Image 1 (spheres, helix red, strand yellow):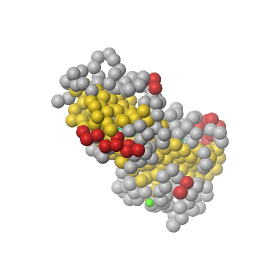
Image 2 (cartoon, chains in turn yellow, orange):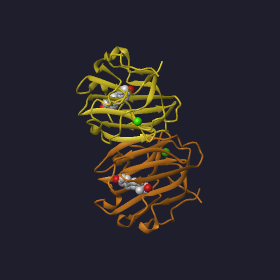
Image 3 (cartoon, each protein chain N blue to C red):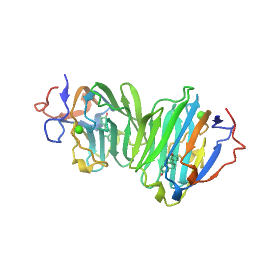
Image 4 (cartoon, each protein chain N blue to C red):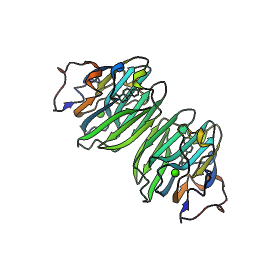
Length: 175
Length: 175
Ligand SMILES: C[C@]12CC[C@@H]3c4ccc(O)cc4CC[C@H]3[C@@H]1CC[C@@H]2O
Ligand SMILES: C[C@]12CC[C@@H]3c4ccc(O)cc4CC[C@H]3[C@@H]1CC[C@@H]2O
Ligand SMILES: [Ca+2]
Ligand SMILES: [Ca+2]
């Protein structure tokens, strides 16, 4: 079962989850995505939308990560185009001080020395938003148009042990 | 004709070129590299080894860029392993405010918003060192052992119009 990553004209995420970082052990997430859209947000995460935030999206068909925290601030593209209408496996892992991006079983990007441990963030509540940002797109380091006309399936985010809340799936729309 | 990227035990580059940035028009370089070595420096560049420097190397077989300037400071891995004993084409381009890395005809990395124009650097003299750094390896954001047991060929760096000086090829060693 797959869900649409955008619902209608709005830019809002289709879903938000929140996690207690004092209870994280697994610091990775995995999902499959399918789209013909070259630009948009796949997911956004933060502990503070002003001071500690992360965005995985597509620009010109390829993955783009933007992140802004006390240790690093960056806008980076990598990997193959994904806007070919095929399902693609994506894994985004925090390992040590690094963020790893794997696409279709291949590591395509490693941002080294970019974060302290999730355990120790100043604010111990992490949000993950699917298909949109939790601030205006103009707040990005490099704006894009967030709407991603795509589908998401087989998605797991950190683990249930850490999860405090998840948005109502009443609004989710099947693909 | 190919040359070795390391000569004996020392860490020093095998060659240094310097350029007048007031005369650059082409801001890209291209070469082929072949190695079985998973770690080392391919080339280093700077306008100031303290304040504005760039390194392309291999770590765990894959490209790594480190760069430190007024606008960005980063350590990033991307692309496939290159330590498979095959010749690989590499192109490193500055385009707008971005650095592009292309391997075997595929863009594998785009560092966006990382530099002002080469035209306008505070110091208008750029050095490019092949096979080594122009400071101690401990000065890197993330140290590696610089010696790269590999070969380089078909290399062009910016253009001759901009070049002020090039090291004596008396020390270069053929592969
Ligand atoms: C933990 C994840 C990778 C690392 C991400 C990160 C990494 C650094 C940072 O300062 C904030 C965030 C928030 C979102 C995190 C992501 C949410 C899911 C993904 O697996
Ligand atoms: C111009 C090159 C790409 C951009 C590199 C860069 C990029 C940003 C910066 O602040 C310094 C340097 C120095 C070395 C430059 C490289 C030397 C050859 C390569 O093509
Ligand atoms: Ca879009
Ligand atoms: Ca080596």
